[PDB]
Image: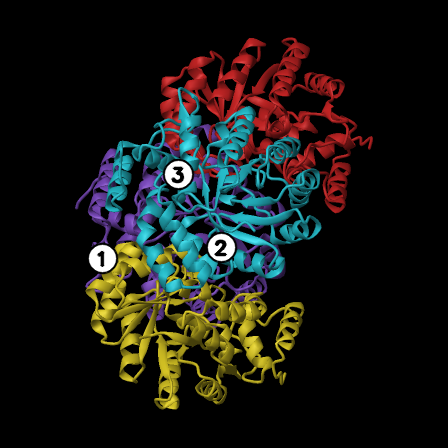
Chain colours: A cyan, B yellow, C red, D purple
């Protein structure tokens, strides 16, 4: 059921606090632009620097604002199982449609550890769970064997956001976990090839600024029209690349600021772009004829 | 122009010499199974252990025996420019339809060195040239910038065999180089996603064993029917994987032996598979109900 | 900061920090000559300790140590504001230094890393040790950034390097002051790093064979690498087995066998596979360690 | 095999091997204390030399050196039959040893790696040095395979290790005999590898500063790492710049600047990017070297 165009929403900041009015407008932005679901408090949403309480407040707020018009997925994981259980329980409590649980970063648990982590959370909270695999950030990877064991034991574990350049891994997951499981692209530039292999959508960064176009790419792929998919993919390629000229979400939050959707404010260790890179970004957005407010 | 199902043909040996009887039968095998072109003396053909002379002989043998019934591409590269020019000139003289020139391995030339290497070969020999990029073996990669410059300056540098797991590189090549350039998959398990991005075919290891099925996969992709492409892809997945249980071409040549197409003979440093892996290979081939003779 | 420093494990007992075990651990190192105790590091399962447990463990280590042994507090994370607060607390309770890991997971730009450490350093007047371990953080603080940081912040005085790149060690030693201190972040690399100029090690092996490791350090610091090699190769098997599974799984299991703590981890960490635990036991018995479990 | 060994460049002139220049290079090393010369190695552009030139260069070197300095012949490739014949030729013409690289590009299995070296070693009674450089060959010979080879063939006596993994060096030193010799395959890692037990280096840097490198090796062999460190750090800038571009592009260019050979490579190798060549010149000037070009 998790499919289509999903946006990894940035978390607006103002006066060093979560900017709820901007977040609210961001939600409306996606409701009227065709986005299928919003992921709040994810990596792109700067969850590392959000307090545990801001996490629960943002999730609760998003659910209330969206109010069923679009799905709301909450980023509820970390590298501590007990903590992930509590936050996932909260998401369940406040009405979130699903929980995105990242593979534990930094402490590099064994595969048995990864199994017990996800199993513990899934058996504790009756909410759809999406595994989030991104080795380039977590410095560890959940094996397909482990994913298979997890999806088989917990009807609760239904999908995986894959931020991996290995198409072979996607093939393995699609083939082994079967049709009731859903693979979601964790990288905009790889959505087309991943969907050609059976992925059901993408949890996108580019979605933050060009919702309609990304949505179109997804529908073309879902329809099996890859001639049209390629057309959109190559048109959006420049955007996909520039959004990563610096560590995500630095570029995407900066782009949203340029479009007047939020304040140009991050929380350390994240910082504003280098003037040179920020100008490259502005120039790319202009080529797409986006209405820049700042 | 170079597209479809192309086989990276093994080079059969017998009594420590090239087995021309077996090589001839291999050519017949591909002529009546619909293969689009035969590539001889590539990595899968054990070019590393073939003398310059055997290279020359295998290429002429392939062209003459093919007798115009199937395209013949000659593997003519190495890591020394002078000899690459010489062998490529030979391929041209004996009527090869094209030359596959690998990115120099081991000596890791600079990008300028790669530019001069390929430019020299292309300008000296008027034969269509396919660049062969495989970083996992050569330990260096020809940048897209270098490829763009070469393709722009040399009319006969028309394609690239890409054995890379980076779909983004494929996107970059398709987008930056003309519609007049052809990208060929250099990895059987990656053919589907690469063609979804615009690749025109594959220089395959698997079609040595199942040419009809692989061509069917290519046909579906070219027609844009990725639903059918996926069915073939996943059907052939076990085959694609087992053929790399040990360094290519050890398993594929062993598979050809089991099918009775060649002797189970390699040239050191290559060796026969371990008894255990060989048995695992046989099990996979039986699963595909292949007519094993050995 | 120099010598044999131990990246101490954090004992657990039925869901909570085991302070009696931790207390014995402190005396264990006071009695064996260890130069300093690092609490709440990766080896101490910092990832699964709440913020309150961090500050609690840090104060407990300082107060129970009572100046008998130097205490270093692991106070970093990937959020600058939190790191400042925890580092301030370490300073507040009297820790001798603060180990601040390079932000993990969010991969800050070098400018971000600069501002991260600068902020903590300028806010808390306590000696700071940068902790670089790319294999876990998935990002690396550049030597250019370290140079700039050490040049501007007088209290940024050292770096724990868990890197297999000896060239990076050479660049740091060469570019940063003679005063700056490079501490090995990998037991297996202590000898080569010290031959290059490193001042010591923040070890994992220290948790079970404090005297032998201290011996390795002394020989290296004395310039007697003939002897350092003798100790290095003798402890080689120990060094390797301690990483048969993700650290601190092996070392805590070893401490348990030695009767130094309960066999309890916090998920996602788990007990070793029975076959790897058997391997660990065999190695320990080979060093004739008095196992109690 | 030990001490300071030079991976000699191969001078070219008008598309042919420049024997006059080569002879002078040999005298240069006899005059400056180099322990052995390796001809037709990666640094000597073996990839672009014909089998014929390989034979010619090796025979020329032995005849010129005439025992005043040891001569090691690069005789390997990724084809076993070919390596046997070239190695046989090296022994025939009087080479003191043969360096056989781990097969590149075709990625043999460990069994193939075993058979490759075993076949060469059993066919030719000449001391053999294994050359492991994963960054170029794209495969690595495991310590297990090395152990099996060294145990089986008395003439497989050493390994040139171009790896940044000190743990691999420790493993080789500990597992293989005291007789087996590990030689650094990277100038910047000679110090740490020797601190671990390596016996010398097959260097690129001593092509231009033979005396200084020799002193580094001597200090290390004597166990005086304080002195080894000052030389290591003194030569760091040189070690670094010699790899600003793929070796041997920088070192051959340096030799040309020193007037030791013509500025000529064989494609696919090319002259340095202009900006990089200028950076190289600056570094050599900093060392006050007598530049002729």
- Which residue occupies 44% across, 26% down? A20
Q: Which residue in the structure is indicated by mark 1?
A: D264
Residues behind callouts 1 and 2 on a single chain? no
- Which residue occupies 31% across, 80% down? B97
Q: Quadrant of residue C293?
A: top right
- Compare residues D100 and B129 and report the one nearer the observer: B129
Q: CA distance from mark 1 to mark 2?
A: 42 Å
Q: Nearer the viewer, mark 1 or mark 3?
A: 3
Q: CA distance from mark 3 to mark 2?
A: 33 Å
Residues behind callouts 1 and 3 on a single chain? no
- Which residue occupies 54% across, 55% down? D157
Judged from the image, the secondary structure of the residue bearing numbered disc 2 is loop
Q: How many marks?
A: 3
Is there a contact, CB below 8 Å, between mark 1 and mark 3?
no
Q: Nearer the viewer, mark 1 or mark 2?
A: 2
The answer to whether one can see residue A26 in this image is: yes
Q: x, y (%) of residue A60?
A: 55, 30
Q: Which residue in the structure is indicated by mark 3?
A: A29
- Compare residues A178 and D51 and report the one nearer the observer: A178
Specify whether B243 is left or right of A286: right
Q: Which residue in the structure is indicated by mark 2?
A: A166
């Amino acid at each position: 059921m998790f499919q289509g165009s999903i946006v990894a929403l940035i978390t607006p900041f103002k006066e060093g606090e979560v900017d709820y009015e901007a977040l609210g407008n961001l939600i409306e932005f996606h409701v009227d632009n065709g986005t299928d679901a919003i992921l709040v408090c994810g990596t792109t949403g700067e969850s590392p620097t959000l307090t545990f309480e801001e996490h629960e407040k943002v999730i609760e707020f998003a659910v209330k604002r969206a109010a069923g018009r679009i799905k709301v997925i909450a980023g509820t994981g970390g590298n501590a199982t007990h903590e992930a259980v509590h936050l996932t329980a909260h998401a369940k409590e406040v009405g979130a449609d699903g929980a995105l649980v990242v593979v534990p970063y930094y402490n590099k648990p064994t595969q048995r550890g990864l199994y017990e982590h996800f199993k513990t959370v899934a058996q504790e909270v009756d909410i759809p769970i999406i595994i989030y695999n991104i080795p380039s950030r977590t410095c560890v990877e959940i094996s397909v064997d482990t994913m298979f064991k997890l999806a088989s034991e917990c009807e609760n574990i239904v999908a995986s956001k894959e931020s991996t350049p290995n198409m072979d891994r996607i093939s393995e997951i699609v083939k082994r976990l079967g049709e009731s499981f859903s693979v979601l692209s964790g990288d905009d530039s790889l959505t087309l090839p991943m969907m050609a292999l059976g992925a059901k959508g993408v949890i996108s960064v580019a979605n933050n600024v060009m919702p309609r176009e990304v949505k179109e790419l997804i529908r073309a792929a879902l329809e099996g029209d890859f001639r049209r998919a390629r057309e959109i993919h190559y048109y959006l390629h420049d955007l996909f690349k520039v959004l990563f000229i610096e560590t995500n979400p630095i570029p995407v939050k900066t782009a949203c600021w340029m479009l007047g959707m939020c304040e140009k404010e991050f929380r350390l260790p994240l910082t504003e772009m280098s003037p040179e890179n920020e100008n490259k970004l502005r120039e790319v957005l202009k080529k797409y004829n986006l209405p820049l407010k700042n």
